[PDB]
Length: 77
Image 1 (cartoon, rainbow, N blue to C red):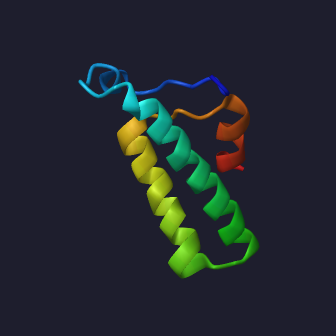
Image 2: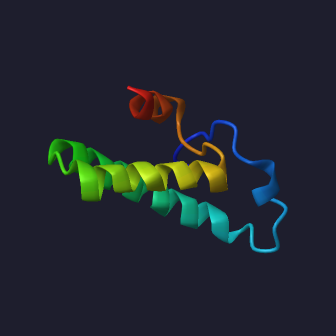
């Protein structure tokens, strides 16, 4: 697809509804990029910056990484 995943969780492919998880997790990652890059630019650290930090964490509890090598570096930096 549009990007190369980088060590997903294997156990998401084995679900009965694994066709849906591709279109879902691409939307959630897009929202995390959008409203984390906005939130740091806005310096909305308590209700917004620490929110989408907490939602990026549960993106990795759920989906593994599933973001680019180019975009893994951006979250790290």
